[PDB]
Image 1 (cartoon, rainbow, N blue to C red):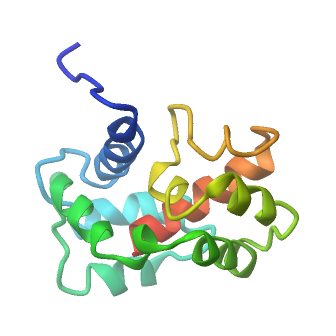
Image 2 (image 1 turned 90 degrees about the vertical axis):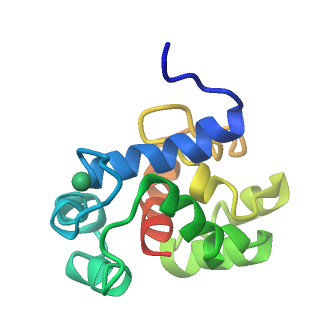
Length: 150
Ligand SMILES: [Ca+2]
């Protein structure tokens, strides 16, 4: 295809970011318009945050470009989280201490957070005994959360 997934890392990271960017910047015009962003926040993020998500990030920096997400999260703690950070955030904000050991030990460190996949296969799923609903939903929405909130 024209769009060609080069490496699995970009498939996870670039495509995750491309997908969320497309969901907010529908036109991917290179600027997530705060009003565009609002629509994706209104449900997917709504499970946690609705107006504050944009008020914190898009407080000024509204129009976020596809590349901007990359640098944004690159310069955000989410991507810098190690195995201890990731898991502490998991039980603290996810409340799933029954799988923290699996993730941590299988070696999860700020990885599956920007490497979850909404439509494609995720990363955490391989690193958990079962690619079950609770696992995917917990991390998909919470990773979506930490990525898009930063
Ligand atoms: Ca747009």
